[PDB]
Image 1 (cartoon, each protein chain N blue to C red):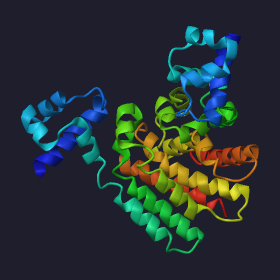
Image 2 (tube, rainbow over the protein chains, first blue to last red; image 1 turned 60 degrees about the vertical axis):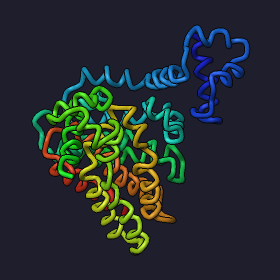
Image 3 (cartoon, each protein chain N blue to C red; image 1 turned 120 degrees about the vertical axis):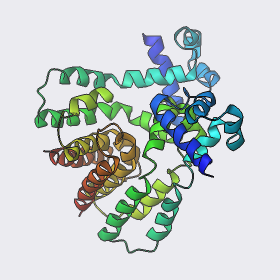
Image 4 (tube, chains in turn purple, yellow; image 1 turned 90 degrees about the horizontal axis):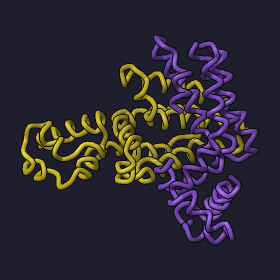
Length: 170
Length: 179
């Protein structure tokens, strides 16, 4: 759907520039131009568009979950899941940025991945460190913004630290 | 008032079991065994119980910030605010679970006013000026592992204090790796 993707692209451009709290359904309707008439055919609420942006950008995450269903429950699998999850959240970097600025977007807003990381019967220390490594990559986009440096250089250094934590669970 | 604390305990248990928005004043009064009029005498609305639950628990955080502006910018200092920030969230783990499972509870308390400006303040004392990107990332990783820790620590099965010590220990290892 080219029109439905164009509604998301215009709204995402305004959420980055103007903010999710400030962007109105009228503003995005004006930026859509002629495609304004297709807006209310796909969505009816601004929250409905933000969820659709999260659904589209969460594409590589859904493939990662389905791929991990067919992997052995080993430490190497957890590490490959953690590396691919870091690359999957790449496209959601602007989405994390509007959450830290808009309180309602954070309220509007991984368990399947945790189920694959979870080791049944493992020690509480090992299980906490597995969740620590997963949370370090997940919430990483929130605090990496304040750090000065190349976004890719910071993402890889965080993934390096998370993997060390993941290895400490064994 | 001892009755006032008993309402908050019964409310917190119901908040966790079925949800803050799902539960009602009717279910909180019936759970304690008092009348509706007796419940409203202590709290005018369900929101006032949630405010009282989250009350006083954030005091040690402000004391941690004022204490941090007093210490030298050394690795032992960063290690100590990590251990003290973990203690400050000891009792706030069930509250953070409520804010996750209820947008109305999150909006009522407010994520920005409850430990967001202070996390930015703790990170400023945490920030090592002129350090490498690898060191700066690992310092922020250790701080974020304990901050966001109280969110996902309720999902892992185990003693709440035993899980906090294991997470704090892991974050300390990450902070040490920044050197």
